[PDB]
Image (cartoon, helix red, strand yellow):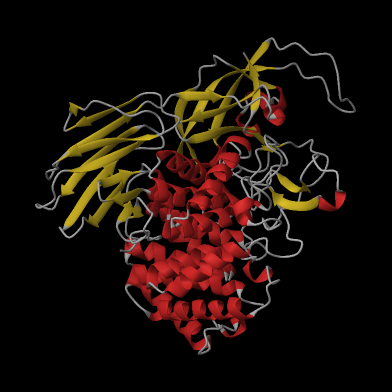
Amino acid sequence: SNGLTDMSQSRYAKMANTGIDAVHWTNGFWGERFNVFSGTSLQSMWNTWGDMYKWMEGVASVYAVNKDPELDKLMDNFIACVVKAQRADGYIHTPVVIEFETYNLGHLMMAGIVHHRATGKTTLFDAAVKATDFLCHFYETASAELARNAICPSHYMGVVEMYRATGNPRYLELSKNLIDIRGMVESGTDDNQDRIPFRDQYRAMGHAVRANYLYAGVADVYAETGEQQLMKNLTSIWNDIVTRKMYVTGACGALYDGTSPDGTCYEPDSIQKVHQSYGRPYQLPNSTAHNETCANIGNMLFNWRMLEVTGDAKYAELVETCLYNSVLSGISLDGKKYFYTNPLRISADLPYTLRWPKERTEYISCFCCPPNTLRTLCQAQNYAYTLSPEGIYCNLYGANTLTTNWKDKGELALVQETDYPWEGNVRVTLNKVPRKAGAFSLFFRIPEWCGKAALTVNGQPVSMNAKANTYAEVNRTWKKGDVVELVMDMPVCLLEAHPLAEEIRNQVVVKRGPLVYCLESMDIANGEKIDNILIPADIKLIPKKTTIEGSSIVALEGKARLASSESWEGVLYRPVVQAEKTVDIRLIPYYAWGNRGKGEMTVWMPLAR
């Protein structure tokens, strides 16, 4: 009835969200993050002073969980200004919200839907339904060659979410036309994924935000139309991204600037510029990885739609990877500063200055991404579970309550206890089961990273059928007070990459559970230089809780090998040096990088096998 995204009536969906109010984080990783975001980040962003509709959507999303009546009033005031400013035909003149501009309207749609779902009130929603009608007029009337109107890619999702929210067929028809038009124009571009029609695209293409939001939006249309061809496109594009063009943190977009295609084409007039963009297959540089935070949110939201349309746990893995490692990295631990880029390496020898700061900044002003970052992070709880007629799916582990209504039957409430992501032990406790529910299942995702896992029910072992990257089902007539307990082994992992990824050939990245780890220069004993650190393949890395900006994180401590250090000044090639020494290093989670001053950082490190 009521989720952040509601595929509950969608004819070719398989799962749908829990209600926007059903899941609260409690006592761990996400509870702690949620207190920062709700109790600091939102105020801090209003104080520095389209962005606002994202902020507000965030306020409503937080409110759905905590019911702070001071937020409800702060919303009613924001909404009053919005409503006072709207015309009869649905337009809004943005200047007259006091205390080709069709781009802001798309964000009003989602703000209004989310507000409706959280508060019950129709005050902002009616402002949104009108804005939507205005866009339908705008696309029925404006010139075929306005690709620019929809250069806001939020639109595709917002319009399908409005059809979902109203039943109004005009909105679904608009969203179908928006796909059908792509590439029915003179000189579209790879960079705007519109050189060729959508149905001819079987690979990821250009500006990664535009790309990924497109792919998401199309999955949303697929949820409603069941047009198989779209899923033929969406599955080779997903495949292209994930096996060939995605950083290990889930982030997307290797190139600040470049050309598409690269080194394959003989008409140079066919070769176009791209920016903030996907690159060649296996082109995954580190220092110059763009990985705009919103592109990574895009990949997350793409994967979430693919999960709901297919029921396949492998899409849930990507939602998690993205959330911890390329979305949460976008904000500081103090909730106040933001990244635009998410590089996988900072070297102080880097002889040019890339665009965009490389320390987080509290300066929303210029970037339109931090509002999207904060509202997304303010909604993490809306990704923990999904439902279907078969039962309930545990997708993102973390300490929480869930209270849904289970069909026309009554409340079902459960309590999830775990120190995830720091440890791999989950306990689901059933508080309320409605008496007339039959047997029904509780599904537990087994992470792709997880090699062993076991279940118990009230202490009694179940046979574990499932493999990595699939759901373990537990079908049972559940009684009040029942207890399921997932134990996932969560060892330290060393990962290598496909040999065609030259930028990381013969190097290793360290995961533990779902967190990608990195090394910063201040965690190397004796200020020994980060470039000289080698990870032997059989290194023994030891978890140890430690504190950064008042947050308890698991670092990994161990003995790396140290390269002898000849000066690299004015030298490109030289005789391989000895590497007889050792040095104490400490790895921290990537997301927590850059909270301890300026320094050096790398995810991928030399491997000694």
Quadrant in which the C terminus appears: top right
Q: Which one is in front, 123 or 25?
A: 123
Could you say where residue 596 lies in the image, as x and y percent from the top left?
Answer: 60, 42
Residue 382: percent from left, percent from top? 38, 54
Is 254 positioned to the left or the right of 420 in the image?
right
Find residue 454 and report its image quarter.
top left
Tell me where residue 589 appears, x and y as whole percent: 53, 36
Q: Residue at x 54, y 23 (%)?
A: 494
Residue nearest the observer in this picture, 407 or 73: 407
Q: Quadrant of the N terminus?
A: bottom left
Q: Position of residue 29 (x, y in %)?
A: 40, 44
Q: Is residue 127 above or below residue 32?
A: below
- The residue positioned 34% from the left and 51% from the top of the image is 15
Residue projecting furthest to the bottom: 88
| Up-down relation of residue 69 to residue 547 (above or below) | below
In terms of depth relative to the viewer, which is nearer, 146 or 381?
146
Which residue occupies the extreme left position in the image? 435
Left or right: where 487 falls relative to 558? left
Task: Determine which quarter of the picture holds residue 351.
Answer: top right
